[PDB]
Amino acid sequence: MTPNLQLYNKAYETLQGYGFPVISRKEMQQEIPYPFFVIKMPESNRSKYTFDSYSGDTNLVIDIWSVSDDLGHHDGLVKRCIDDLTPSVKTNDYDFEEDDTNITQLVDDTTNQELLHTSITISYKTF
Amino acid sequence: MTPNLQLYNKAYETLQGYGFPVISRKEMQQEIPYPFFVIKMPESNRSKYTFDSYSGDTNLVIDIWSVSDDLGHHDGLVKRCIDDLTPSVKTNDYDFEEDDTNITQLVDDTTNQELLHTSITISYKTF
Amino acid sequence: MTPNLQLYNKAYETLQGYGFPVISRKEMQQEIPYPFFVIKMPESNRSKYTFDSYSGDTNLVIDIWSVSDDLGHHDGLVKRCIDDLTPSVKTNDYDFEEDDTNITQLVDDTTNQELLHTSITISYKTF
Amino acid sequence: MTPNLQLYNKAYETLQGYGFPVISRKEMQQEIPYPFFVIKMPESNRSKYTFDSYSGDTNLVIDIWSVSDDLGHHDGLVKRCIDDLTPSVKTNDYDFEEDDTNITQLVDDTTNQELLHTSITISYKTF
Amino acid sequence: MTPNLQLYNKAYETLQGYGFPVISRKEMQQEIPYPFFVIKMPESNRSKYTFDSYSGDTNLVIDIWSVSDDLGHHDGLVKRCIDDLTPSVKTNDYDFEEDDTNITQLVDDTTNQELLHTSITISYKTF
Amino acid sequence: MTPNLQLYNKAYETLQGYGFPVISRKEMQQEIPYPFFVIKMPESNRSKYTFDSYSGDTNLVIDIWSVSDDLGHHDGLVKRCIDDLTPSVKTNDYDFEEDDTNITQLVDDTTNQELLHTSITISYKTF
Amino acid sequence: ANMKNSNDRIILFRKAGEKVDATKMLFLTEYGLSHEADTDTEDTMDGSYNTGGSVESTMSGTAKMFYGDDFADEIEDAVVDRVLYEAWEVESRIPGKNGDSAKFKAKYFQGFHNKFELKAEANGIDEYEYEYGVNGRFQRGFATLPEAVTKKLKATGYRFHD
Amino acid sequence: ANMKNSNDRIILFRKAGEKVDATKMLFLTEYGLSHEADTDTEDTMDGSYNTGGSVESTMSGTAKMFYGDDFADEIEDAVVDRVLYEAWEVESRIPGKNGDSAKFKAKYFQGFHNKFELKAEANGIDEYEYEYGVNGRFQRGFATLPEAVTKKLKATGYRFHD
Amino acid sequence: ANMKNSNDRIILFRKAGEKVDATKMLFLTEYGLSHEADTDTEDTMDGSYNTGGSVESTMSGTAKMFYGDDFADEIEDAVVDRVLYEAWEVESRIPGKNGDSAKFKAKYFQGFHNKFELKAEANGIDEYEYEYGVNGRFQRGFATLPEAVTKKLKATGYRFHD
Amino acid sequence: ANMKNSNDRIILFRKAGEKVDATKMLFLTEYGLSHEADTDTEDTMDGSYNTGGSVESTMSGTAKMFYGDDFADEIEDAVVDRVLYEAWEVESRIPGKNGDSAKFKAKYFQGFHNKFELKAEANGIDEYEYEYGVNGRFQRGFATLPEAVTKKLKATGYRFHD
Amino acid sequence: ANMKNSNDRIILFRKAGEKVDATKMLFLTEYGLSHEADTDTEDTMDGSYNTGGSVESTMSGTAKMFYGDDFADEIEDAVVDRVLYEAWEVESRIPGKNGDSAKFKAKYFQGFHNKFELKAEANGIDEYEYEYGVNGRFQRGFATLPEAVTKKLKATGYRFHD
Amino acid sequence: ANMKNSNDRIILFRKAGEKVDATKMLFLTEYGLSHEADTDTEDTMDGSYNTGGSVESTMSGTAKMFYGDDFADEIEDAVVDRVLYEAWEVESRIPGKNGDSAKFKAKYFQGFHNKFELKAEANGIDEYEYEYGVNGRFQRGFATLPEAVTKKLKATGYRFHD
Amino acid sequence: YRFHDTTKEDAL
Amino acid sequence: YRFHDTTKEDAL
Amino acid sequence: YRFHDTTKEDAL
Amino acid sequence: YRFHDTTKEDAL
Amino acid sequence: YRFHDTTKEDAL
Amino acid sequence: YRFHDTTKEDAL
């Protein structure tokens, strides 16, 4: 596997354990209750790093949708993700270490309902 | 909680004390007199800072809407916000320190009325 | 007051003395002869500068509209503004010092008449 | 030949061996099963590098389309490409060495079907 | 006068001597033969430069329109402009010195005729 | 002449010798067989370089259109151009030296036919 | 949490031996205090050892000059006339425990100013920088801040105030 | 894989000769340990050769100061008073094999602090940096980490915790 | 507020011993005045002490050359011929109190020019920079500005004027 | 064409005089080998001439530390204990011609490690860098690569493998 | 206004003692002329004083080499053969007043070239730089420019011409 | 016009005293040739004067290493074994006038290589750089280029060819 | 020397 | 000197 | 030396 | 010293 | 030395 | 030393 799929599988194994639905994209016939997680396949740069290995920067985005009725709970999901996915993730072929994490939130009215949209970006240096 | 929600709650506890209405977004059936405050959920970067802690940059935007009939009063609200939210904000888990604050104002005619729109951005380094 | 309103009031007190009309925006029922001045509320950055003070960059834009029949006179207004607003402006709470000034002019045909539009930007460091 | 066509021919000779169809663009009367490879003609910068040679940066993009039913297999194609095209490619006139490789994936719904689109970029320094 | 109008008048006094028409913008009832010059009011930055003077960067654009039937002549106009406006321009209040000049040409078909459009930019440091 | 027209004439004298048609733009009544060359008037920066001369950067673009039936031949035209126009071009008033050359190719379907479009950029330092 | 800002340090000076209240160093831009031991080491075929030489100690800083002032003019008199100066570094947010309740934690130095440079550049407020050479062991204690300077004479605008 | 992060090193100090648990150096920003041999070479017409001079060894670092602390205040006392200090560098993720099962791989030094600089700048938390001069051969071993400091007193927020 | 701009300093010179009005240094780009004490320290087993060596003092600057001028030509004569020069630094916005009402606060130096470099580069106005070595104690006072130079001969354009 | 990549050099070490296979220096980041002649020149009124002084030769490099390792721990023992080390630089892609068919072109050195610095920084894998002082003439030859290390123990992921 | 461009200085050379017209230094990129006094100061308990040591004077520059030339080849002969060279610096836009009406203001030097470096880099025209050591006092005067070089042999293109 | 590109210089070497054709230095990245006079000056109360010391001359450069090569291996043998080397710098585009019609303008040196450093870094072709110390006066002349190397063995691709 | 407070009441 | 552990039970 | 004013009336 | 191969069979 | 003009008519 | 050409026919 690439580091992309290895990390993506670890992030699914994690977020899929909380009991809320986790998806890559919603299909039209599929009914999803709030809150829910969208998780998007990582990007990965690679370059020569030592005479014996590559290294690179692998970017993960996970994306949390909720009704705005209770923001303390939505923030509980954000903090739960970050605490499970940092400082380091470890898998069969690869190691990942948080370089930075960026949290941004929007109030979204596209759906005739006031939703909260949090986008969590984590940059992992990988070895 | 994240630093985002901790700061956002402190900024509400503050601005909600002045006696003008404070909102994150206006809903259609909700009547809001002028002047009023819009307050938007912070962004937060994070990175390793010492062998013992993270640190990062947390960005707050608060946003003041008024009719242009009296600009000295609208500026009184701007200065009152800045004086209550700087130089430092302190909460249960986090400390915040002003790195910079940016004030910009526009004259807005979108609503068939001449409004004043001030956007106050405060960048906090956080520890 | 903020430095924004302090400077904006000083720039009005100045330009309003020349005898041409000065406005922030033109309203539909309001008749304005040429030439006229549009003046726009400053932007202001702020940051810690010494152990005892902030300092920052405050940006003023004033904006001169005339029919193109006589360009020597329009340029007389531009030079008169710059000579009254530089090198320094001084007010009750704040000092302002020209960092740079930028003059740009366009020939404007939006109004079925050939107008001259000069935009004068002055960047003040402030203390 | 240019380094562009030399590399492009080597990348075809490679990817065309896996047994899936490989194309530069799909024509309307041409039926292509999934998965398939799109391969795009390299860009090449050139500059003087020694008193005796040029050198430069040659950019290859190969682009993998699949139905999202099985992502482990699609990732198997991505890893197979990268392992055959790196660290170095060698041809009659030119040498190529991986400077970096960038992998990005999207979930694509443009075609009323949920496809996976992976874009693999490899930057070769060339000599 | 500003340096803008001083330079603009010197550039008119120059280009207006060649015998082709020179304009800032063409009006609808005005018939202009080819070739012709469009000349656009300079931009000017200013900043403190010594304890005794400002200095700054003043940008001139002159703009040459011709039918493409004879390109040697159109290029003769371009070279004639540059040779009259460089290396230095001198006027009552100001000095100007070429920092750089940029020549770009396009083939223009907007007017149902194949025209040549040359834009000549000259950056003057000014003292 | 400018360096623009001097170089443009040398690039015409060259490419016009191969026996394929060379044009700056195609006119509607003009029938052009494939393959063909489009050649676009250079850009030129200029600045003071020694106490005795200017120097500058002059940018040439030549642009090769072919049906995609045979890519080895189209690449033969690209390589033939580059080998005739580099490393140096010499003319009456000016010298030109390759700083870099950039080759990019696209597959173009704008014309209901699959064409190959190669854009060759050569940056010449000039003296 | 509880990180320590630079601008909470207060630097004070007075000319040694004259009975006056210490004067605050306004508009510091940057600051540093350095201690460094001039140790040698002596080699022998039984083995090398390190020998405890004397310590040099010094305080250093930069400030912006202003018109309502006379203190940079005292620093440049002091460096040339070799005047002995007392100085304090006080931590404006650590108060003393009891009895010293109105005082703040401090270091006390006395010594000489050894450098003063004015730096002036077009388009800029002119800086000065200085160096101060500490005599002997600096002394630990608690210092009274001059309350009329630090909290009574507040000013509006970008000057810091409560 | 298995790359070694810097922040897994734990640096500990105590004043030599007093019976107390070692105190952890919190909020290190950067760190380094250096060893360097002062070799000469002697030329002769039979041929040149290299001679085995003595080795100088030193430990160096930077930290952020904070209000709940008294240790930078000990470093600056120690550099001036020439106090001998013991120090450990411990690898928080290499445990001892057996018997030492509760301990972590370490180097033990004793020596003197030889430098301390405070650095303070407007808009910034003030740093200190130090240098420590090792006496003799540093000694290899396994070290007990002070478990009450390293794992019991955890704190929320951006302070690292499990 | 009341920050001090660099360009309010006026630098004046004249050749020592000739009865003429001081000439202004036009088109300064940057400037500096430095004082620095060459202190040693003497160690003893009773304790080390710091000894009050002599002070070196110097003035330094850069200017743009222009065609209506003869003064850089005097600086480069003066550095080679070792001519003694008087110089003033005057603060154009601090006036004297009474009697000195028409004068401005100043330092007076006399000394020698010790350096002059022309710097010329293609695409640029050529600079010169100089160094001046102060003899002895600089003297404080109030200085008359040459009013015909400073306020009567004003010029239009980018040259500063009221 | 045929340009020579850095990562095709293999650097090997072993402690001198003990019968063991050489150990590979893993995770080099950068490397250099230097030779430099300490020539004087002697002037005379008949004319100056250049005199052939002795040559100093040294090898230098940086590596990333990792947990499955014990070799940086040997370098830092070796610099302090002045242990003599053999070292090879081998060119992994130039094979020997015949008889040496299984060997690769090499330089052989013996000498002492003279420097070791750990560098650790927050948000980073800690580096070490070293210097090695060559004794005498380095010797040319062909070297057997330790095939179990270089080709048998391959690993997946970003570690280089065929 | 009236700022002084660098490229209006003309630098001329000739080999000392041979009756030929001075040759212009074409394609200068940058230039500088330096004078600097090696003053000591002598301390005494009556007070320190500054002593008037001798002055070193030197001219320095960089140029682009070209094929229609033989002059850089003369500089590199001159630095090795220790040939004495005369040189002028002439101000191409200050004419002499009367009698000297056809001449331009100048400095005259004689001295030796003391440095010459070629600098060559792939993708570049190769530079040379030189240093010239002035003997004694440089002499002021007015110089005739070689009119056939400076105004008659004009050339088209990017070479400067009227 | 007629500006001189760096890559038109050809640098050649051979070991002194063996009858073989000179070998070209391929893949130079940058190059320089330096001459510099070690002049003193002697002061006297009658006036100072400058004294004509001896000249040091040296050639320097960087190249990329490649697999079809044995010459960097000769440079590193030569610096250690103190082998005397002849070298040429030839100008590939200035031909000789008559009789020398097939030759190109040149400098001839003989001397010793005095430095060689390999530089290797991950993600890069490894460089070497060298220094060569010229003995005496370099000699001017015209040199035959080795036509089989320079024009017969042309190669395709990014290697320069006609 | 010992410690002395900032104020004129504790002059040197 | 020999190795001593961090704790007060192994004081110098 | 003492202070002397800028003007020719206070020449050295 | 002469050349010695990397392996234990050619120990110093 | 005195001043000498650039031309061969004022050779050293 | 004098000048010697590059070729083996003009060896040192």
Image: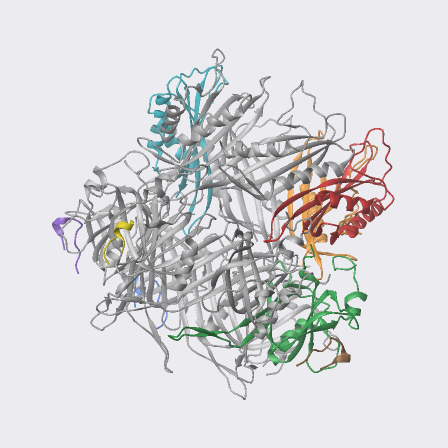
Chain colours: C red, D cyan, E orange, I green, N yellow, O brown, P purple, R blue
Q: Is residue C34 visible?
A: yes
Q: Position of residue E82 (x, y in %)?
A: 69, 50
Q: Is residue D39 left or right of residue C11?
A: left
Q: Position of residue E37 (x, y in %)?
A: 75, 42
Above or below: residue D4 compared with residue I111:
above
Q: Is residue I24 left or right of residue D125?
A: right
Quarter location, residue I159: bottom right
Q: Residue furthest left?
A: P9
Above or below: residue C52 compared with residue E109:
below
Q: Is residue E9 visible?
A: no
Q: Is residue C58 left or right of residue D95?
A: right
**Along the line of sight, the residue nearer the viewer: D6 or I100:** I100
Q: Position of residue D90 (x, y in %)?
A: 34, 38
Above or below: residue C109 compared with residue D36:
below
**Along the line of sight, the residue nearer the viewer: D61 or O12:** O12
On-image quarter of the N terminus of chain C? top right
